[PDB]
Amino acid sequence: MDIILGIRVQDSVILASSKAVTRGISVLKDSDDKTRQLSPHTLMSFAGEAGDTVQFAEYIQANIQLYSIREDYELSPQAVSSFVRQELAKSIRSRRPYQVNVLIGGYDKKKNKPELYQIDYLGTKVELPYGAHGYSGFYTFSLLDHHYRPDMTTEEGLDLLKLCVQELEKRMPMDFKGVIVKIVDKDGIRQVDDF
Amino acid sequence: GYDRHITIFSPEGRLYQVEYAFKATNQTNINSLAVRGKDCTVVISQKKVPDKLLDPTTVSYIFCISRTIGMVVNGPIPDARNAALRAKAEAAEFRYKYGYDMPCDVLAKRMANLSQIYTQRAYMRPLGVILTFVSVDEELGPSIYKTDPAGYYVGYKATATGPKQQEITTNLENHFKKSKIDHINEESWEKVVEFAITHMIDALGTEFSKNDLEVGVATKDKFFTLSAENIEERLVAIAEQ
Amino acid sequence: TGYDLSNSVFSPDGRNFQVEYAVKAVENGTTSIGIKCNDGVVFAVEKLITSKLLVPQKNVKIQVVDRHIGCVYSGLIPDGRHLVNRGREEAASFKKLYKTPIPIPAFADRLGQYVQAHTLYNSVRPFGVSTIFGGVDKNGAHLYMLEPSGSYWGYKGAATGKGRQSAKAELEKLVDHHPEGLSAREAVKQAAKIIYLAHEDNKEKDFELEISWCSLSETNGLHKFVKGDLLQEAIDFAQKEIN
Amino acid sequence: NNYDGDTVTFSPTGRLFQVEYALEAIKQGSVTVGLRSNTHAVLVALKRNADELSSYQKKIIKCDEHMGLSLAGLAPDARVLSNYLRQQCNYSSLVFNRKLAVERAGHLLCDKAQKNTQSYGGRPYGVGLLIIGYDKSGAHLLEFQPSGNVTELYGTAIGARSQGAKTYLERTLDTFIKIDGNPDELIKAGVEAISQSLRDESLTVDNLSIAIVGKDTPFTIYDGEAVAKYI
Amino acid sequence: SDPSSINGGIVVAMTGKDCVAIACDLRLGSQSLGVSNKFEKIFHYGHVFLGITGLATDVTTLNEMFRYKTNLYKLKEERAIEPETFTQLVSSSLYERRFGPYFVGPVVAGINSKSGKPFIAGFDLIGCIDEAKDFIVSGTASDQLFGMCESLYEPNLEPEDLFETISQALLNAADRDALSGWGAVVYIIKKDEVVKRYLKMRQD
Amino acid sequence: TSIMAVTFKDGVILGADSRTTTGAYIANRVTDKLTRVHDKIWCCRSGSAADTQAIADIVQYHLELYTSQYGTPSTETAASVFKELCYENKDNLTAGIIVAGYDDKNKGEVYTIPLGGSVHKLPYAIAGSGSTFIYGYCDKNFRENMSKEETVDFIKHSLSQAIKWDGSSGGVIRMVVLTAAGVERLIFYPDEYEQL
Amino acid sequence: MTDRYSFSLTTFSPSGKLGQIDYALTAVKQGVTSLGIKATNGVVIATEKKSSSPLAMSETLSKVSLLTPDIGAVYSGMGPDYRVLVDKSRKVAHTSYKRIYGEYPPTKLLVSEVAKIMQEATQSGGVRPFGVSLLIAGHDEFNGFSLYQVDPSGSYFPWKATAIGKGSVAAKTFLEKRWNDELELEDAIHIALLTLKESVEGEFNGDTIELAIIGDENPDLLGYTGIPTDKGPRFRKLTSQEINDRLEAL
Amino acid sequence: APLX
Amino acid sequence: TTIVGVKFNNGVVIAADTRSTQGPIVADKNCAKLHRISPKIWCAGAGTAADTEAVTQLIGSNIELHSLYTSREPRVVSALQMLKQHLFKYQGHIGAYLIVAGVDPTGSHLFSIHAHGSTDVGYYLSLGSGSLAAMAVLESHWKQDLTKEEAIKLASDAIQAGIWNDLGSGSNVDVCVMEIGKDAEYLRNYLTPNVREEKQKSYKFPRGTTAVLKESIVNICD
Amino acid sequence: GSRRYDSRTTIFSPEGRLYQVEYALESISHAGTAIGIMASDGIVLAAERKVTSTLLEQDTSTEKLYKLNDKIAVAVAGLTADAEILINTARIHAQNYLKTYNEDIPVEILVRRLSDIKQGYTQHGGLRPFGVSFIYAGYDDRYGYQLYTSNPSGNYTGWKAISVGANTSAAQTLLQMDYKDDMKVDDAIELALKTLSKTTDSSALTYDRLEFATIRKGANDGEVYQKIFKPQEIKDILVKTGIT
Ligand SMILES: [Cl-]
Ligand SMILES: [Cl-]
Ligand SMILES: [Cl-]
Ligand SMILES: [Mg+2]
Ligand SMILES: [Mg+2]
Ligand SMILES: [Mg+2]
Ligand SMILES: [Mg+2]
């Protein structure tokens, strides 16, 4: 785990997540996909404590998929984010809390608008034009404060994202082995293979 | 007709199990009486020991619930003792929780509430007993409060219970019509006990030896029962007048 | 009707027929007695010898509770054992909390409330035993008899089982002829006689006599079984009286 | 009639019909015999089959090294009760380093059976047991009935036609009680006892079941060719 | 790792002549890192306003909880909850979590629709009601707010004047606190009109 | 605290100081540490004020319920109920209690129950922080079968010394006399006992 | 042992009747008459004190009960059932309202809680319904004065005026002729006494009649002074003497 | 806390 | 906090200051520390503010139900017993330090309760951070057979000692007098010796001083 | 034991019917009629009060029509006490959903859960079923205006127009006759009142024996308003259609 980023542009939400899985002094994997599709137009990336992350992600995925089958309907990104927040808000006062931070990128088909939600392990939710978890934010937020515009295209968003990854690869102590980038828009979720 | 077996309503809105519990009340064939003085409350009850092999000292239907509260029961002894043990426990708990002695009327209400539950809940049968509680309450003074299997309870100027209760009741009514007051205008409890026995003799039309009666007396800060010789002393005083 | 089919149901008389039916089981059982004496109590019971194959002296029916109380019963023997097991639990918790061994009147009410509780619900059956019990405490000797309804009183003498009326009549004579009191050793002898006299009501099978006693002077206030010379002496006294 | 719907109901004459019906299941069961001397105690049991293709239902169960029983009636109920006895014998060993007295074993079974005769929902046990054992007071034989009644005896028998063996043992009492220090003769007496309960069938090699416990003999069961000696 | 100062934020309430004002900053951070400048801390249920400072997850949770409870109240009672009644509901709810409390500093503000009386109140994290004629303060710059309010406040201010006083109290308090600021919102509340104003403040 | 109970010819007398402490501050200078659990069974309380009050209240309740069913409890029985509470809750209690009562059969009896919840029947008992300073004095001066006046003087002189040396003890000396005659309360003020 | 009655004792019959509720209502019919009348500035509730014996002190048995300082209750049917309902009703006013909101519940909501308790006795395992109908009179700031009837089923209805029990049919007809929307509290008390005389047979005085009002605040009955907002209970039980004064100008 |  | 209780001829009086603090800061300059348990039973509370209010209300609620159940006026010893057993159960974690006082059919009463559940009896008591300043005054001026007006004077003087000498206490003096046979009289702000002086200047701003980015009407209606 | 007195409320008949459910429906058929009619621009709820007395307080009364949330209401037919138990559960369920998802609960989800509770009482627990039938009227942004009904079996279905309680057979025939899809709210109001007026067991339909409610988008722009009619408003609407 470690680096997860999110950028909401005019017509889409872009999530970038690091590929490294490190344990001790060994990088065990350099192609890890730190994300789960919750519904056709909703994607969740995650970072935090080992084991907890995937266990939480898949648990949420199962619940949203269950809802989709029951109602024959897709929950809005706002509705999914609120469900996720409540689960984390419950968790923080449990015997053993989920130590998982998430970003939720979704496209609301009723509003025809992209939406990005940042939720930490405490259950602290905010809707943002761009988001980050962990030490990543200490570089990317100021960078995006400068270069981000609300009317950008998906391509402009990807170039803006390249600028963030380059900065992280320059100034971050750890080798996070690049990122997997995924786009969420009106047509659903797709992965950029060459980043 | 299973509506007569458990405590549910019959078509005419009655509870037959409660009514039959009232009939169990007279199974012992014993009559009790309670009156109030100025300073005291006296309760008397018949004592019938038919078997010669019985230890007469252990045959009793009067109970010391607390230091201040006494209780006489009309009904079978197993149910009587069940009620007595519960009353003792309730009175003790009340004192511990609330820091003062449980009043006679409050205990009566509590036991009446318990009885009410048995008339509404199916798995519990009513107790076939009528409970007469007596004391000298520190706020209300001399007190008589009586409970039945229906869960009914009320305070009394005086009262009687048993097979020949009506004869005793009217006898007492006619006295209070005459005296024009709510109690026995007497200083000592000894003479209030004498009044109680005298009017029971008149109403029932029987004479009593020392072993035919049972007497409980409530005064300020204690309730106590009388011995055979205490009653004999009392019987002699009535005869010499 | 149908009032007698379920326990805890009042009949139109105000009676619990199920308890009265349990009394019939007690009346069917063998004879047991209790005699109160000067400084203690004596218990005796009739043991029907069904067959030669029964080992003599080895099917003991009288039971001790704590170290100072004896219990005997007539009717359904297993029901009696259940009651004694409860008695032993009640006595143990009393001694645990209050240190002193449970007084007999206190113990009597513990059994009484427990048996009475088995007349309150239709999900339990009343006890099919009448229990004669007692012992010695700080206030002297006490004898009690407890019935299926939960009713109990103190007794000068007590009897239950198939030969209860014969035994009661014999007990009443002792109370009349000994107003000052009966001694412990005398009460043992009398207990034997009364069981032998009460055996006339169960005389197909011959029987085995079993006696126990608690006495302040003779047994030091503890429950003991009468055995050996004292038992044979009591048997001989009884044998002489029937002839 | 109207009073046999459950165990919690007394009849007007003070009978428990469900307990009596449980007693009836024992009478239908195959005969088993118990007898003892002063040194040994012996169980003999006639086993029953479904047909010629089936096995013969095992009647005898070991409870400890010094105790065991034979059954007549519902076999699963015997399994429950024997398992309870195994645990009680075992509790006595682990906690007190003490072999459970055969008399206490009887008291424990009585109280377990009794509880099933006084509560709603449950049913009585439908099996009778003959418990033998050797403890600190010598050899013992007990008879368990699911009414709760347990009885110590020199000898006895339960099951169908058990009256024949029970009469025989009543006659032979003075003889077999003094068969001390001789296992084979005490068994012979038990095998002759159970023979008084046979009709049209005789004791074969896969039909007879014998068990013995004593002074210098752990509770052991004999089946198959090991009982050919006694036919 | 002090729950009440991880996210930062402040709320202040004031009374005037036939009116009340309640204001809050917009910052949500994670210790030094500023994360959001749109995080409003004032909510309303009918005409009753509630501001909440402290741990942001509990701020959100409690808003959702009081929306829940006031909605059921209105359905059963067939009327809107009043500030005095809502104040009691907040106190009960917080004390229910006595030994595992929400790490918050709530502030009630509103006008009783029957009597017309302006009402404000404050609470600690476990429910203790703090009623005041003048002002209530809460958050990571509460010391600063106490100082500003105590000096700037005077009774019976007109709605337009009260706006200036409460705004200057919040702004100057926020600028002396690292974890507060990043924007501000002020609610001016009259008997049957409510005006909401976003303030221009320094963004550091 | 300084507390004691002393058996004598006619029965038993309980004694105590009147100081409650909250650090070096005296929260109550007129405390009553001699407490009724039954008509003629009383106790001296030392240790935690809250713990000893809660225990005494529970014991009083138990003996009141005992009396309703079985009549007057023995002093031994009362001590057994104290023990049961003190022993089973030893991890959560700070209570040093002396139990003292008068039977007509057994006369005066004293049972002391220290921190662990053990029971010790003694002719006399001393307890509380101030008791340490009078072990020597009490051992040398106690005699069995003393008179009422002698026993009162013994307790007065003993607690006077305990109070003199123990900062955690002081105020008035309260005493409760338990005999066949009844229950008598005695009080002794500083001006008397200080100059002994 | 243990409550094995985990099943309903009230069930639907083929015709759709709930037998035990119907039979409970029959028990209410046998009960002594009680009534309630709502005025513009108050509410009155009244009933006959049927004495079980002349030796009994009827003052110790209260048929009209205070639930909150502004809410009172009276009944017809089984007294013991009523007594425990009053206990439960007083407690639920605190547990489910006062301990949450710091104020007493409005009449309609307390009535709603009592109704719930009575509904559960109609459906839960091993219990019979309550054999009583209640009349609950009360006041609260936002609803003013109100009067409610609660039946064994758990159903409740608001009334301008009504009667329940023995002679309720005749009493309701009497109230229809006399009731208008301009009645002052004293006029409602007068009509209550007139209506009750029809159903009462024996003695008709302040010792055989029980009557309480929900009216103005009573500062003298509060027990303390110093808090301006606390002005005292609106519930007041009329004394034996106060009833007799109104029976002369009858 | 209060001690004795 | 400074709180006191003083017994007199025909009843009892309690008093308290009106400062509540959070660390060194004064949150309320006029809070009410005098609580009503029942009409004629009042209590003064120091320690954790939410605990004193909550425990006072809970026992007050149960006392009301008890009063209705028993058809009797509540007794001070009942409130005392219920409070102490509640507090003892929580082993001091509920930080309520109370002075309980009132009149009932038994007479007039004055008690104190500590957080761990111990109770004391007395003719004069004081609790809170200013209890030593108050107790110094009480020990100096208290006597047997005080009149009503003397007891009020003594009580308020004891509170004033706390107000002036204890930093934890300040502002005003509240009093409640509970006399036998009469209604309890709650005297809110009986003394107000700490009135703020006139400010030197008005800090009313010229309208328009505050820079504004956005305005909008808020919808409160349905 | 207690077996003797068990009615066995959750068993099948030999024909495969649930006795208690059937008998609960028989009970409901004697309750006051309630009608729901769904129009393109709103929903009407109309219900007849059970034989009224002149001394009944009519304005401060609620018997038939209850509010579940701001977007959903129900008309009741059966035992009112039973209905209030279910209504409070439904009210809580709506708030749980709003708390979880920050969106108002879709109508069907609320109806399904309430119907599932009813189902449970017919399959397990040995308790009598709820003697209640609901007409649900509500709006959400997925399906818009919706009418549902549920009954003691826990079975629910959707409708354009439906009646519950007494005389449903006659009422349904009349609704089936005059209902058409392009209908407006004001027309539906008239149809509802006309149908009750003809199916009523009373002599004449008056304002004091009716409860009435509408759910329109007749607020200001893209939002829904619930109007529970006051007595005087029912009096006026009864005159406006010429019934009185
Ligand atoms: Cl109760
Ligand atoms: Cl103390
Ligand atoms: Cl100490
Ligand atoms: Mg019942
Ligand atoms: Mg700042
Ligand atoms: Mg900065
Ligand atoms: Mg000193």
Image (cartoon, coloured by chain):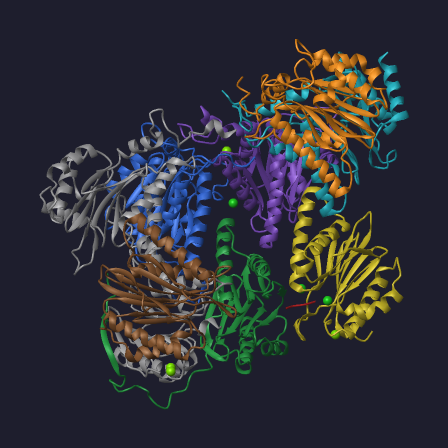
Chain colours: A brown, B purple, C cyan, D orange, F yellow, G blue, H red, I green
- Judge whether G19 appears above or below E196 on screen: above
Mark count: 0
- How far across and down, in percent of the image, does residue J244 sit? 11, 42
Q: Is residue E121 left or right of residue B66?
A: left
Q: From where the camera sits, is residue C109 visible?
A: no
- Judge whether B148 appears above or below C240 on screen: below
Foreground pick, J83 / I204: J83
- Judge whether J85 appears above or below G1 on screen: below
Q: Is residue A39 left or right of residue D98?
A: left
- How far across and down, in percent of the image, does residue C130 sit? 69, 26
The quarter of the picture where the C terminus of chain D appears is top right
Extreme residue toward the top, this view: D200
Foreground pick, B36 / F39: F39
Extreme residue toward the bottom, this view: I200
The quarter of the picture where the N terminus of chain D appears is top right
- How far across and down, in percent of the image, does residue J199 sit? 17, 35
- How far across and down, in percent of the image, does residue F107 sit? 82, 51
- Judge whether E152 appears above or below G28 on screen: below
Q: Is residue I139 left or right of residue C52?
A: left
Q: Quadrant of residue E14?
A: bottom left
Foreground pick, B203 / C241: C241
Residue at 36 percent across and 26 percent down: it is J13
Extreme residue toward the front, this view: A194
Q: From where the camera sits, is residue A61 visible?
A: yes
Name the quadrant where ligand 2 sits.
Answer: bottom right
